[PDB]
Amino acid sequence: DYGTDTCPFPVLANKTNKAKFVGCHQKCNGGDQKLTDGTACYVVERKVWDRMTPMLWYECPLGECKNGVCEDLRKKEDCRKGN
Amino acid sequence: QPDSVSIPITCCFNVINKKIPKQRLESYRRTTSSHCPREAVIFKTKLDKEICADPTQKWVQDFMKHLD
């Protein structure tokens, strides 16, 4: 009823404070929310995201979304999580 | 220092298709394109479920105005 793809999606942000999404898929109102292919993402399992300390600089791996998966682009950057 | 910028924990990727019935709506929060990839408004329902909405749609501006 609220759509299966209108939930807010977890992010992280690098030194520019501009956010990128964490992973490429989540459950949304009991459905499967999938980000478009090519979207930049952090290759980070969600249970990890959920247990991170806000504002701590972490070494986050980057990737792009493909068919609901954050495919590792083999490069890294420091990122941090909101409060 | 310790940095005092506020970083969002979630951003919106897609928004709702039709206006939400007012009787459901409980709260809102606004997502800045300064940090999020696209600016959006996040309504929170009486069941504490969160819905992404387009800040340019007329009905959003009415409702978030309603909630003040």
Image (tube, grey):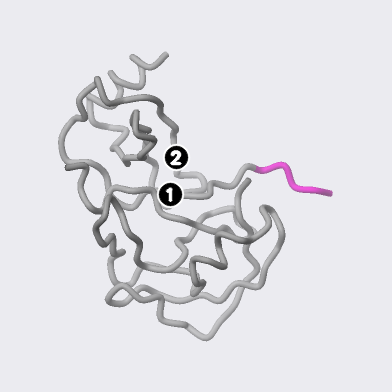
Q: Mark 2 lies on which chain?
A: B
Disc 2 element: strand
**Residue at horizontal 32 percent and vertical 33 percent from the top:** B55
**Residue at horizontal 39 percent and vertical 35 percent from the top:** B48
Q: Residue B26 appears at what percent x and percent y?
A: 37, 24
Identify the mark at residue B31; answer none if there is no mark.
2
Q: Residue B8 appears at what percent x and percent y?
A: 54, 46
Which residue type does callout 1 highlight? Answer: Cys
Q: How many residues crowd mark 2 within 10 Å: few (<14), some (14–19), many (20+)? A: many
Instruction: Tell me: residue A82, above or below residue B60.
Output: below
Instruction: Tell me: residue A51, above or below residue B38.
Output: below
Q: Residue A19 appears at what percent x and percent y?
A: 51, 56
Q: Residue A70 appears at what percent x and percent y?
A: 40, 75
Apparent side of residue B58 relative to residue A49 in the rendered image (left or right): left
Identify the mark at residue B11; answer none if there is no mark.
1
**Which comes before the other along the chain, label 2 or label 1?**
1
Distance in Å between CA atoms under marks 2 and 1: 7 Å
In terms of secondary structure, what is the magenta stretch mainly? Answer: loop
Question: Mark 2 touching mark 1, by CB under 8 A?
Answer: yes
Apparent side of residue A5 relative to residue A77 in the rendered image (left or right): left
| Residue stretch rendered in magenta on the structure | B1-5
Please tell me which residue lies in front, A41 or A5. A5
**Residue at horizontal 52 percent and vertical 86 percent from the top:** A74
**Residue at horizontal 43 percent and vertical 68 percent from the top:** A23
Please tell me which residue lies in front, A52 or A77. A52
